[PDB]
Length: 166
Ligand SMILES: CC(C)[C@H](Nc1ncnc2c1OCCO2)c1ccc2c(c1)S(=O)(=O)CCC2
Image (cartoon, rainbow, N blue to C red; front, side, top):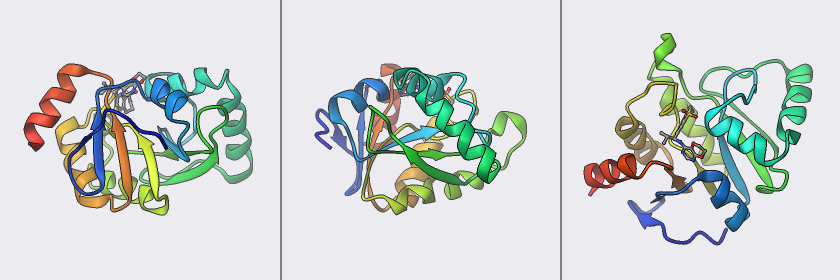
Protein backbone atom coordinates (compact mmCIF):
# COMPACT_ATOMS: atom_id res chain seq x y z
CA UNK A 1 0.00 0.00 0.00
CA UNK A 2 2.75 2.55 -1.02
CA UNK A 3 0.35 5.20 -2.27
CA UNK A 4 2.14 8.37 -3.47
CA UNK A 5 1.04 11.78 -4.71
CA UNK A 6 -2.45 11.59 -3.19
CA UNK A 7 -4.29 14.66 -1.91
CA UNK A 8 -6.01 14.00 1.46
CA UNK A 9 -9.64 15.17 1.26
CA UNK A 10 -10.91 13.91 4.66
CA UNK A 11 -9.45 11.71 7.48
CA UNK A 12 -10.05 8.60 5.39
CA UNK A 13 -10.49 9.70 1.73
CA UNK A 14 -7.49 10.44 -0.59
CA UNK A 15 -7.59 11.38 -4.33
CA UNK A 16 -5.10 11.28 -7.27
CA UNK A 17 -5.29 12.02 -10.98
CA UNK A 18 -4.12 8.60 -12.13
CA UNK A 19 -5.01 5.42 -14.12
CA UNK A 20 -6.14 2.78 -11.49
CA UNK A 21 -4.27 -0.04 -13.39
CA UNK A 22 -0.97 1.84 -13.30
CA UNK A 23 -1.55 2.64 -9.60
CA UNK A 24 -2.28 -1.04 -8.83
CA UNK A 25 1.01 -2.12 -10.50
CA UNK A 26 3.11 0.47 -8.62
CA UNK A 27 1.33 0.24 -5.25
CA UNK A 28 0.43 -3.54 -5.19
CA UNK A 29 -2.39 -2.79 -2.71
CA UNK A 30 -4.11 -5.26 -0.40
CA UNK A 31 -7.46 -4.47 -2.20
CA UNK A 32 -8.30 -2.96 -5.60
CA UNK A 33 -11.95 -2.12 -6.21
CA UNK A 34 -13.56 -2.97 -9.56
CA UNK A 35 -16.58 -0.94 -10.82
CA UNK A 36 -18.43 -4.15 -11.84
CA UNK A 37 -21.86 -5.16 -13.27
CA UNK A 38 -24.07 -7.93 -11.70
CA UNK A 39 -22.73 -10.65 -14.09
CA UNK A 40 -19.06 -9.69 -13.62
CA UNK A 41 -18.56 -9.25 -17.40
CA UNK A 42 -15.60 -6.88 -17.63
CA UNK A 43 -16.02 -5.59 -21.20
CA UNK A 44 -14.80 -2.01 -20.95
CA UNK A 45 -14.07 1.03 -18.83
CA UNK A 46 -12.40 0.38 -15.47
CA UNK A 47 -13.52 -3.30 -15.43
CA UNK A 48 -12.11 -4.03 -18.91
CA UNK A 49 -8.83 -2.25 -18.07
CA UNK A 50 -8.31 -4.20 -14.82
CA UNK A 51 -9.17 -7.48 -16.62
CA UNK A 52 -6.80 -6.73 -19.51
CA UNK A 53 -3.95 -6.13 -17.01
CA UNK A 54 -4.51 -9.66 -15.57
CA UNK A 55 -4.51 -11.02 -19.25
CA UNK A 56 -8.10 -12.23 -18.82
CA UNK A 57 -7.44 -14.20 -15.53
CA UNK A 58 -9.95 -11.94 -13.71
CA UNK A 59 -12.63 -12.79 -16.29
CA UNK A 60 -12.04 -16.60 -16.04
CA UNK A 61 -12.28 -16.40 -12.24
CA UNK A 62 -15.37 -14.15 -12.42
CA UNK A 63 -17.15 -16.63 -14.75
CA UNK A 64 -16.46 -19.45 -12.18
CA UNK A 65 -17.86 -17.23 -9.35
CA UNK A 66 -21.09 -16.59 -11.32
CA UNK A 67 -21.48 -20.31 -12.18
CA UNK A 68 -21.43 -21.23 -8.48
CA UNK A 69 -23.13 -18.25 -6.76
CA UNK A 70 -25.26 -16.54 -9.36
CA UNK A 71 -25.18 -12.78 -10.17
CA UNK A 72 -24.62 -10.03 -7.62
CA UNK A 73 -27.40 -7.60 -6.68
CA UNK A 74 -27.06 -3.85 -7.58
CA UNK A 75 -25.41 -2.34 -4.50
CA UNK A 76 -23.67 -5.66 -3.66
CA UNK A 77 -20.16 -7.11 -3.95
CA UNK A 78 -17.87 -10.11 -3.82
CA UNK A 79 -14.17 -10.54 -3.00
CA UNK A 80 -12.08 -12.43 -5.57
CA UNK A 81 -8.29 -12.77 -6.28
CA UNK A 82 -6.46 -9.56 -7.23
CA UNK A 83 -4.07 -11.63 -9.41
CA UNK A 84 -0.92 -9.55 -10.34
CA UNK A 85 -2.67 -6.23 -9.45
CA UNK A 86 -3.46 -6.69 -5.72
CA UNK A 87 -3.92 -9.40 -3.02
CA UNK A 88 -7.76 -9.13 -3.54
CA UNK A 89 -10.22 -7.55 -5.93
CA UNK A 90 -13.43 -6.26 -4.42
CA UNK A 91 -16.02 -6.27 -7.26
CA UNK A 92 -18.69 -3.66 -6.39
CA UNK A 93 -21.86 -2.99 -8.35
CA UNK A 94 -22.95 0.68 -8.35
CA UNK A 95 -26.35 1.61 -9.89
CA UNK A 96 -26.41 2.29 -13.62
CA UNK A 97 -28.63 5.39 -13.37
CA UNK A 98 -28.66 5.72 -17.25
CA UNK A 99 -30.73 2.44 -17.18
CA UNK A 100 -33.16 3.46 -14.41
CA UNK A 101 -31.41 1.91 -11.39
CA UNK A 102 -31.98 3.87 -8.14
CA UNK A 103 -29.30 6.37 -7.08
CA UNK A 104 -30.02 5.40 -3.36
CA UNK A 105 -28.11 2.14 -4.08
CA UNK A 106 -24.88 4.13 -4.53
CA UNK A 107 -24.70 4.39 -0.69
CA UNK A 108 -25.12 0.53 -0.43
CA UNK A 109 -22.38 0.07 -3.07
CA UNK A 110 -19.87 2.26 -1.12
CA UNK A 111 -20.82 0.47 2.16
CA UNK A 112 -18.98 -2.64 0.82
CA UNK A 113 -15.66 -0.73 1.09
CA UNK A 114 -16.08 -0.72 4.93
CA UNK A 115 -15.10 -4.45 5.20
CA UNK A 116 -11.48 -3.60 4.09
CA UNK A 117 -9.04 -1.39 6.04
CA UNK A 118 -7.30 0.07 2.95
CA UNK A 119 -8.51 0.14 -0.69
CA UNK A 120 -7.47 1.55 -4.09
CA UNK A 121 -10.72 2.42 -5.93
CA UNK A 122 -12.46 4.22 -8.78
CA UNK A 123 -15.43 6.65 -8.33
CA UNK A 124 -18.48 4.31 -8.43
CA UNK A 125 -21.19 4.75 -11.10
CA UNK A 126 -19.22 7.67 -12.73
CA UNK A 127 -18.69 5.98 -16.07
CA UNK A 128 -21.17 4.80 -18.62
CA UNK A 129 -23.31 4.30 -15.40
CA UNK A 130 -24.19 8.04 -15.73
CA UNK A 131 -24.11 9.22 -12.09
CA UNK A 132 -22.85 12.80 -11.40
CA UNK A 133 -19.20 12.12 -10.41
CA UNK A 134 -19.22 14.97 -7.83
CA UNK A 135 -22.31 13.42 -6.18
CA UNK A 136 -20.57 9.99 -6.22
CA UNK A 137 -17.61 11.57 -4.38
CA UNK A 138 -20.00 13.07 -1.77
CA UNK A 139 -21.62 9.63 -1.16
CA UNK A 140 -18.10 8.15 -0.84
CA UNK A 141 -17.00 10.74 1.72
CA UNK A 142 -20.26 10.29 3.75
CA UNK A 143 -20.31 6.48 3.68
CA UNK A 144 -16.78 5.16 3.63
CA UNK A 145 -15.15 4.97 7.06
CA UNK A 146 -12.05 2.89 6.17
CA UNK A 147 -9.06 4.32 4.22
CA UNK A 148 -9.83 4.79 0.50
CA UNK A 149 -7.41 6.03 -2.18
CA UNK A 150 -9.43 7.10 -5.22
CA UNK A 151 -7.75 7.13 -8.68
CA UNK A 152 -9.58 9.44 -11.20
CA UNK A 153 -7.97 9.13 -14.63
CA UNK A 154 -9.32 12.46 -16.11
CA UNK A 155 -7.41 15.63 -15.07
CA UNK A 156 -10.43 17.85 -15.95
CA UNK A 157 -12.73 15.79 -13.68
CA UNK A 158 -10.04 15.55 -10.92
CA UNK A 159 -9.73 19.37 -10.86
CA UNK A 160 -13.53 19.81 -10.64
CA UNK A 161 -13.69 17.25 -7.76
CA UNK A 162 -10.89 18.93 -5.79
CA UNK A 163 -12.44 22.40 -6.43
CA UNK A 164 -15.89 21.19 -5.26
CA UNK A 165 -14.45 19.58 -2.16
CA UNK A 166 -11.80 22.21 -1.23
C1 LIG B 1 -14.84 9.03 -14.97
C2 LIG B 1 -13.67 8.32 -15.66
C3 LIG B 1 -12.53 9.31 -15.89
C4 LIG B 1 -13.21 7.08 -14.87
N1 LIG B 1 -12.14 6.39 -15.58
C5 LIG B 1 -11.11 5.76 -14.98
N2 LIG B 1 -10.82 6.08 -13.70
C6 LIG B 1 -9.70 5.54 -13.22
N3 LIG B 1 -8.84 4.72 -13.83
C7 LIG B 1 -9.17 4.38 -15.06
C8 LIG B 1 -10.31 4.86 -15.71
O1 LIG B 1 -10.66 4.43 -16.97
C9 LIG B 1 -9.63 3.74 -17.71
C10 LIG B 1 -8.81 2.84 -16.85
O2 LIG B 1 -8.32 3.49 -15.66
C11 LIG B 1 -14.35 6.15 -14.52
C12 LIG B 1 -14.80 6.02 -13.21
C13 LIG B 1 -15.81 5.15 -12.89
C14 LIG B 1 -16.44 4.36 -13.85
C15 LIG B 1 -15.97 4.48 -15.17
C16 LIG B 1 -14.95 5.36 -15.50
S1 LIG B 1 -16.62 3.57 -16.49
O3 LIG B 1 -15.66 2.55 -16.85
O4 LIG B 1 -17.02 4.48 -17.52
C17 LIG B 1 -18.04 2.80 -15.81
C18 LIG B 1 -17.82 2.32 -14.38
C19 LIG B 1 -17.60 3.48 -13.45
